[PDB]
Structures are given as C-alpha cells and as structure tokens.
Amino acid sequence: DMYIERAGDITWEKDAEVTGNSPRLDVALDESGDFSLVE
Amino acid sequence: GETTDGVYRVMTRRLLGSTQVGVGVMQEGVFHTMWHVTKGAALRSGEGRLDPYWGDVKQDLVSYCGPWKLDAAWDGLSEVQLLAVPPGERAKNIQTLPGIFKTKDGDIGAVALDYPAGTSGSPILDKCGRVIGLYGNGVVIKNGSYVSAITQGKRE
Ligand SMILES: CC(=O)NCc1ncc[nH]1
C-alpha cells in the first residue's frame, strides 16, 4: 500500500551546486519502456 | 489528503520499515510520477485515495486524479535543475547542462546525474521553475555512469 508525503516546493535555486556532463548518445526505446545504447 | 502543489515522496510499508520507492509532482490537482515507481497501483494521501487516470509503460509515465498537466519543454540550450528527492534525505537542487538521447523518432534531453533508484520521478526544471520532465528512466553508458532521459508527457 503506497502513500505520498510532501517533500517541498518546486522552485529553481539560485547558486545551486552545478555538476554532470552532457553526453550525446544514440539510443533505442523498446515497447517495455527500456532505453538501450545503439552501437 | 494533501493536494498542495509540489514534490512528494512515494513510500511503501510492504517491505522492511517504510521504504521510498520514488517521487512525483502534484500540479493542478493531478499527481504525476513514472510508471515503474507505482506499476499503476492506487496511492494513499493521508486518509484520501488517488486513483490512476492515465498511464503508458513505453513512455514510463502515469497520472492520478486527472490527465497529465506538465507541458514545458527543455529549450535545447540552457542548464536545468534536477530537484532530487533522495530516500531519507532533504530535497536538493542540482544544476546541469543536459546531453541528448538521439533516437529514430527524434532527440530527447538527458541528464547525467546518478541518484538512488528511489529518486525516480524527481522533477527536472527550467529557469522559470516549470517542470520539463521527470528523472529516472535511462541508460548506463561505457564509463558505467547513469544518464536519465528528461521524460515529459503530453498535455491533451
Ligand atoms: C535503467 C534505469 O533507468 N535505471 C533506474 C534509475 N537508477 C537511478 C535512477 N533511476
């Protein structure tokens, strides 16, 4: 039995921690909603 | 139950203690999350019940109480923020420049941030605070790192 609990407002934060790269990938999406890499 | 707009954890007491299985967005009286978080089951909010209204396994999305309301889109150029809600931890904003998933049916923004599975359904936002999609359906690349699509639904 699943239940929800509020965690916060949805807002943009000024000076938030900035990280992560920006990969450009060729991908495929199957009927089950799974993404896979195309090589 | 609680119907105030914002981000919410999705919990279960089926396993040991209370376990966070995902996250979602309440907007315009509709609860939005990824299908793999709830598998389309009903949800509880205090003494109230939220029933599924729309869902799609291939998109990996589900809405409760009404139709999918989120329609903002990544501009393809700017940094966005993941409003990560990790299990047992406070909501935190992480800013990043999305990459791209190139598919036979078009390009989708993608964020290269790795959080616990229970963070699935956390919203990705633009500079105006609009939700441009949900985090948690993606792929593991050569480096072994996780890259999530920015998954957005259609507002009918
Ligand atoms: C293959 C896949 O989408 N993994 C699930 C996930 N891991 C962390 C967040 N979401």
Image (spheres, grey):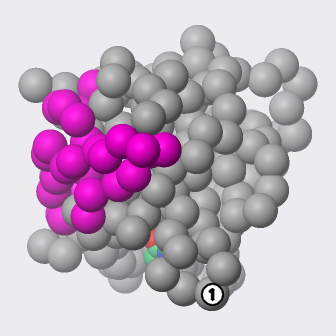
On the image, the x and y values in percent for residue B110 come to 50, 51
* Left or right for B57, reference A20: left
Q: Is residue B51 magenta?
A: yes
On the image, the x and y values in percent for residue B144 come to 65, 84
- Chain bearing tag 1 is B
Identify the residue at image location x=89%, y=25%.
A15
With respect to residue B62, does B104 lie above or below?
A: below
Residue at the front extreme of this rendering: B47
**Range drawn in magenta:** B41-69
Which residue matches tag 1? Answer: B16
On the image, the x and y values in percent for residue B152 come to 33, 40
Identify the residue at image location x=27%, y=58%.
B42
Using the image as rendered, state which of residue A22 and residue B61 is in the foreground. Answer: B61
Using the image as rendered, state which of residue B35 and residue A33 is in the foreground. Answer: B35
Q: Is residue B32 magenta?
A: no
Rendered-image quadrant of the N terminus of chain B: top left
Residue at the top extreme of this rendering: B128
Identify the residue at image location x=62%, y=32%.
B80
Identify the residue at image location x=70%, y=22%.
A12
Decide if residue B115 is in sight here: yes
The secondary structure type at the circle numbered 1 is loop
